[PDB]
Amino acid sequence: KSNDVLLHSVTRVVTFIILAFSVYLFFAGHNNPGGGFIGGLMTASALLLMYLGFDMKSIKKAIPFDFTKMIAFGLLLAIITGFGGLLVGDPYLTQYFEYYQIPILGETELTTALPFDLGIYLVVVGIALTIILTIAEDDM
Amino acid sequence: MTVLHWATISPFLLAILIPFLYKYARRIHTGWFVLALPLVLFIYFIRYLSVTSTGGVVEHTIPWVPSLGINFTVFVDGLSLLFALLITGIGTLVILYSIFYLSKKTESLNNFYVYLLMFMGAMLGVVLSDNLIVLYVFWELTSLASSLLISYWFHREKSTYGAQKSMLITVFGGFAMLGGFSLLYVMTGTFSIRGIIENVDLVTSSELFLPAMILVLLGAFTKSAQFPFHIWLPDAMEAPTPVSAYLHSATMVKAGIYLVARLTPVFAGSAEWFWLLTGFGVVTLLWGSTSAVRQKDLKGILAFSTVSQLGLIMTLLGLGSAAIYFGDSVDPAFYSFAIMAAIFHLINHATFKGSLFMTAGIIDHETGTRDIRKLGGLMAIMPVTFTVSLIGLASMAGLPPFNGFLSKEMFFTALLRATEMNTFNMETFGIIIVVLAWIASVFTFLYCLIMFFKTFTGKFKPENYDVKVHEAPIGMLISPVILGSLVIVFGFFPNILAYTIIEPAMQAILPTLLADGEVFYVNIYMWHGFNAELFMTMGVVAAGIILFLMMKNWAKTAFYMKERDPLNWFYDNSLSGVITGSQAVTRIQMTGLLRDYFAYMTTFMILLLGYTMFRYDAFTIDTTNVTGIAPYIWVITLVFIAATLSIPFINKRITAVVVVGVIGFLLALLFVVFRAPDLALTQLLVETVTVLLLMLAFYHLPELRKEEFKPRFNIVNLIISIGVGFLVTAIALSSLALGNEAGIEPISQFFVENSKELAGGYNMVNVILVDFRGLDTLLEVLVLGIAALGVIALIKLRMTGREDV
Amino acid sequence: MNNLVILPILIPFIVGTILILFAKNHSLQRVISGFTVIGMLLVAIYLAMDVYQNGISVLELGNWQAPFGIVLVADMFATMMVILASIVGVVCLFFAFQTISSEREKYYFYPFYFFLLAGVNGAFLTGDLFNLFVFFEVMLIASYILIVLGGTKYQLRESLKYVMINVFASILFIVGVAYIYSVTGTLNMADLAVKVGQLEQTGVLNVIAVIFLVVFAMKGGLFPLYFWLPRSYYGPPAAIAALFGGLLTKVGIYAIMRTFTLIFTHDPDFTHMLILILAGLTMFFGVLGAVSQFDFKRILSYHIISQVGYMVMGLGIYTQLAIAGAIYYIAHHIIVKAALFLFAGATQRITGTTDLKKMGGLLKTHPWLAWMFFISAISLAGIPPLSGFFSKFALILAAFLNENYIIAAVALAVGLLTLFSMMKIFIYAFWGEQKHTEQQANFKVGKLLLPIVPLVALTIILGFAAEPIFQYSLQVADQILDPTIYIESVL
Amino acid sequence: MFQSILMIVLVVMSISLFVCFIRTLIGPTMSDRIVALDTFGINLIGFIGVIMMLQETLAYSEVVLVISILAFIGSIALSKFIERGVVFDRG
Amino acid sequence: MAFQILLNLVIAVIWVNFQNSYTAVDFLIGYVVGIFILFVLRRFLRFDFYMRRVWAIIKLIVLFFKELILANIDVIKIVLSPKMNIQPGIVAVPTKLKTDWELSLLASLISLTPGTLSMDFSDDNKYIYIHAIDVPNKEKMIRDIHDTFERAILEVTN
Amino acid sequence: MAFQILLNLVIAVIWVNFQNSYTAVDFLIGYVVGIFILFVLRRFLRF
Amino acid sequence: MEILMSITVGVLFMVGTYLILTKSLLRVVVGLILLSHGAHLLLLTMAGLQRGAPPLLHLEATTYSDPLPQALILTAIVISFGVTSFLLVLAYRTYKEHKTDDLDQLRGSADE
Amino acid sequence: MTAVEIIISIFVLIGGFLSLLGSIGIIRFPDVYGRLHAATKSATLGVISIMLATFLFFFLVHGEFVGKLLLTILFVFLTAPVAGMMMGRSAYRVGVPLWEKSTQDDLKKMYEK
């Protein structure tokens, strides 16, 4: 009933760009604006724009994530990361970082803050999509 | 824990075993197992006569909660021994009677004997406690066990009405008494009564002396049914009769008399003690004797009788307190006489009144009625019941040669001595007491003639009664005949009691009156010649007989038509009123309207923050230590304020969402001007998802409306809104200024120093979130996760309310 | 280290999350939930013994020292609140196993139950004021769903008011933290206590004390800030009303106690007098609400308001004896008030109703329920020698020793009104002729009563064994009435 | 002088936001309001670009890119709401 | 086009090793010879040489910008005129462009060009509905769509 | 497939500047990020 | 500037309070969203505004704006998002069941 | 003022002027369809011109190639036409009328079927 040729064309290009930008925002958090919350909301915005631009049945086949398990796994990833210090006799939620050397890449900083912030990120995407999709599909 | 401790609480231990005995030994009436305990505690206590009657006392203590000064101390003296023998002696006899009055087939003996042993152990605990808080603990368990017994037939409305009325009046008094006992501690440092009596000067010097006395007498006068708290006692007659005999005539109604006699050495010696005891006593004496005359159920008459006679004993304790005022300016014998009469009358009373409840019970049991209008002629049909009844009613009327004549003659003696007192305003009021007491003695005699002639004389009318009428079984008769026998024995041989029982109890009540090893003289005898007190008694007899012969006349009066006490209207209306008033006060708060709730809360906040800002002079502004406003911030801020003020005037929801967006975008712009890039980002992303959500909700919600401007409603709303805004700003400005004066280095200079070195990042906000304050971040995603799982539950689970409970 | 301090938060948090993965499996959900509440209780008891023997245990999360990092502080007061939440957590869950529909199990009932408990324990244990806000939000959002779950029409209209009012109180908390941050530049409760005392609680620091009082008074249920409570608690199933009745207002009461014994202590002529007045008004208006009602579960909901009044009465008096009375009162109220809602649940199972005018005669059919209700109900009313008596008596005695006569009198009169209210439930529902059917007379409730038995036992034991409980309360009162003990532990 | 020009342009940008906001209030139609809203958000990117030159910082370069994305998601959703009353099709 | 770009990068990748530079400017020298390599071999292979299309695109980007500047000049005249002198309307304009990405390019160019705004597409996609600010001059607009805008799209298209 | 490889390099072009590292570490992160994006969108974009 | 922002907070509190005292469900939810905005703007203003660079240490500035409030506000915004979501769904589920958005009609039985 | 500052100045003064023009146009055009001309064209070039100035400023004055600013230019170009189309077509479908003095409406026919 509506010719959406232009909305569907643009939504396909911008989604690529928003997702890439959401991953950058997630990894940049430690040293620049971004992190789990901002990255997660930005990623959620990309999936929402796909739902807005197209329709629920098509986009649910296309991106068939279980957003509820992503909440539970998000939370457990973030809790577990916090037990790191119990290995080295340190209080819960002690965070660690070292500059390792990898030949392939180069000097690289590893941090427990990355998996911790990945857990935050998964919950944030999971809850945004669970909330918005549960309402949008509320028949009754 | 001595044996004397164990005896004291032994009835609670047997109460735990009673339900098993009933279950697994039903063959036997459970009372046979209960009877042994009061019977061995009687014999046990009888062994202390050797110590009390030689001037001794026995005291033992074990700490219970010594951090609050509460110790379980048992104390045996003359006063306490006397009440322990009544409680266990008459207890024995009432259990025996209850074995033949309650059939084991349809009666819940388990409930009955548990409540009754609860009471019995609570009553011993009251009279043997030296610690006032342990006495409070047992005093409230008697009120509890008492109401459980009044309610024993809990399916009947009268039973439940009486159980409530007793519990409320007596616990009201008990709560006040606890306040009284706490004031004694504040004066003396001890809840020990024997130690309070040692420090009695710290009591009588104190500004808390009279409040402590009133609060204590509130407890005593509720439990001993002194006017106007006596209204619970007639309504307690719904109990099974053994209970009326034991609790409500012979023991628990004498707990207030016990407490007043026990604390006479703290409080006596003053006009207020004298008058509170003597006046409340004499009104109760007169009110109860007059009310009894119009009662038409045997137990009604006997309940008002007991009220009356408790008022007689309370008046003697009141008259006797003058011994302490005079000390040794007078012969100790003189005013101590009233205290000897009080003790003697309490004993007598327990014998005739316990016996008369037991015969009223037999008459109900064997005729089906207790209504003096339907009884008549039972002298020949029920001759043992007739004889015990005759003896009790003659003793109660103070006819010789029974125990009650001696005590009533000692009462008239005490009263006439008090008229000689020439202190306490007795020069004026002495004869009023004597006359009011004399009138009450005439009404006592008359209610005893009414009960005797209407019940036992005339012609036996076999058709009034459903059942054929016969005397009671011997088992039922033993308890009233043993009590009736003591009426006679103490009448002829009163001095069995004189140095065994009565004199030691006098020493407990007047301990400073005599040197150690000095005994009071106690010689009780029937004939003292033609003195005033004999004429007063002849008086009472004549007046009583005249008024009885004139009853044809006054029975048609409006006074005789009613029987319910006129103070009951108060009780009843006050209760309906607590409920009505409660409901009115509660409805004005809990209106159901969310606006009222926010307006009450915000109004309270404005008044309290407003008052605190004025009281501490905290309205202030610091215009120097502020940063600059670029000219473009004046315009941004004006838009932000205009957008915000437009919201209450919008009436279409899509406009509302758009202007909320504007506001959201502008708050992100301020976060950029204020150097908060991670906030700008977050604020923008949250605002976007909130706009999708508002529209997903708008599919379900209706459109906005212009709601009409009720003048009062919306001007109050406006004034509250401005007052919240104004106070948030004023307190913001005052906090800025104190913060600037103070100059405390913020703790966040540590994050400036150590974010990169100790936590490896350059973004201080992210480092705080995941490292220095990472727990908050982990808790905040848990908030989101709960909100998401909550949204699923709220949309998908729809229950009717009949599924679970 | 002191990593034991975080176990009362982390067990329910971890198990809660794991139970979301097992939403379909109901048997496995119950077994995990059951072991978990029992181990919370043994962890809580072990933490309390440790702190009792070895002093305040402070845990610095992330290994950052206070005031830079979030600390958790297990002192004797916090560890008592952690045990009491654990007892009612166990009992209300074993009662939920016998009563809730399997439909609620499908929608995250058990994870929400454990996230509520984590939130409550974090609130007791945190030494940081913004971390207290966040733990209050975890508690509150888990209560927002538990109170409405089922979405009956009543639940939706009342839950809706509960959530709006609570959202508003959470905003005022943020406002308060804004102003105290401006003055002091710290969020750590110890560091706050030091800096507020350096500033002498001057000027606007009084106004800020009052904003914290109001915020915590709204979460505690003090007058006139309780309107959210009485209608809302009616809606959820008895196991949840018991847990809400017993525990959730205590988190606001604990915060008022912690804040006005540690931080705002410099002008008690003002602040603690204001708390005494709101105490007295809360006792009084609470109990009038209770007296006005003729529905078992609605009467108990107003008694919550009344009884918290007594706990702030001891903080208002502000002596060692009054404080120790309040600490004992808190233990007594959690236990008794959770038992009472559990008895109203079992009464509704038997009769189908909570309306007293439709009930009667349960004493004849269900004596075990009747006598357990009666004992809990006279404990609530202060009848000795149960827990209720001793705890009331410590408060009035402290009031008389300090010459606070009016609040002593209000606390006695309110006791009598409470007795009147509990005797109305007994007269109407347990005494009387049997108003329930024959099938209802033969319903066996012992499986529902067994979980409540320990709470009944504890009101008796806390009465008889009052001397060790009262000596513990005195030591708590000593610890908290000297801010420098907590301060030196943390800084 | 360069900084003087940046201040003048920030004032003009502020006035532009003011003028867009007027149509978000007065409409007349809902379409008019969502157009003004869309233009308000685009103008915010201008305002931030110039704030970045005045403060001489790239801390805000992610903000301009987010605003462009969000102003777009906002307009598409409000346009569909107005026309159909559903943000998401199929559901 | 994607084949050739990838090939070219492979040629540069290898070439920079051979030329011992992982330095940047060498990648360009390398890529350029990859271009000449591909250009020389385009006849040898079957290649529509990719740089013709890359140039077509650069010129389309330039046109997007040129038309936007002109569009704003048109708007300035109208908005700063004492009286709005506009005669607006909706015109259906035919298109030959068949693909979705070409239609999307055209609809976007129309809306950035002077006087016009893409409203809607027919169902069959054979018409683009255009809101025009001056309908009298519609013949110029229809001529520009046909002879400038669709000509420039089809160079990048085919 | 040539399309997807260039997309992935286009993602890495979009990526590399943001970090401004111009190291092997960041370009390898960048090329991989695009693999993950392309995988997530494989069905959307019918790759 | 802390003065002007303290006044702007005043105005969000005043309107947000006015809206929560109305009878419309939607207007109450909006009032609650404005009060949150105010509280968050208050927490930033109370820390001091425009006091140095954005808090990014690689900018090697002399003074940074205070980062601790910025992290508090982030948390508060994120919580508030969670709660507002839950509240909007609770509001619409309430409207659907009662067929009214007027809070006067949601009073319930008196002396319930 | 340096020659770089002059070039950057021109771009910021154009960008700020076209932004204002776009807004004045949202006020002065007679219906939502003409107001979309201003929104889609002026707001768009205005913001493109400021992002160029910002881009040229960090490059020519700080030597930083900030490619996010260019990605913002690209998002604005991609998005501006489609947004104006979805806002104008939504208006037309919802019944917002063309201006009274409008003289042609080919789209009315189509929406007749």
Image: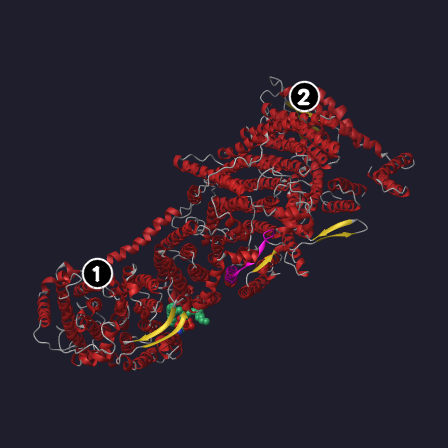
Q: Is residue C410 above or below residue G103?
A: below
Picture quarter containing residue B117?
Answer: bottom left
User: Few, some or many C-alpha atoms within 10 Å of disc 1 (few <14, some 14-19, many ≥20)?
Assistant: some
Q: Is residue B677 magenta?
A: no
Q: Which disc, if any, is residue E74?
A: 2
| Secondary structure at numbered mark 2 | helix
**Count of numbered circles in the view:** 2
C80 magenta-colored: yes
Whole-Å distance between the Cαs marked 1 and 2?
Answer: 103 Å
Q: How far from the left and from the top, in percent, is residue B357?
A: 23, 72
Kind of residue at badge 2: Asp
Residue at the outermost left position: B530
**What label does residue B565 carry, if any?**
1
The one nearer the camera, H20 or B474, is H20
Q: Which residues are magenta?
A: C66-86
Q: Residue at x 81, y 42 (%)?
A: F2
**On the rendered structure, is B242 left or right of B667?**
left
